[PDB]
Image: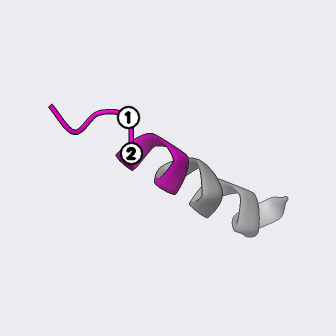
Amino acid sequence: DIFGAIWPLALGALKNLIK
């Protein structure tokens, strides 16, 4: 299912947090 496009998203969110 949609388990590849939602990955780069959560990763980009944790980056703007403290990265």
Q: Residue, x 49% and y 52% (percent of image)?
A: 10
- 11 vs 16, left or right, is left
Q: Looking at numbered disc 1 in the image, what kind of residue is underneath it?
A: Gly
Extreme residue in the right direction = 19
Q: Which residues are magenta?
A: 1-9
User: Does 18 sit left or right of 17 as displayed?
Assistant: right
Identify which residue is drawn at 53% across, 47% down: 8
Q: Position of residue 1 (x, y in %)?
A: 14, 31
Q: Measuring 63% from the left and 58% from the top, which residue is drawn there?
A: 12
Residue named by callout 2: 5
Relative to 10, 11 lies left or right: right
Say few, some or many: other residues with alpha carbon within 10 Å of mark 2 (under 14 / 14 to 19 / 20 or more): few
Q: Position of residue 9 (x, y in %)?
A: 49, 55
How many marks the image carries: the answer is 2
Tell me residue 7's x, y (percent): 45, 41
User: What secondary structure is found at the residue carrying circle 1?
Assistant: loop
- Image location (x, y in percent) of residue 14: 64, 55
Residue 12, placed above or below residue 7: below
- Closer to us: 19 or 1: 1
- For the C terminus, the quadrant is bottom right
Task: Provide the residue designation for mark 1.
Answer: 4
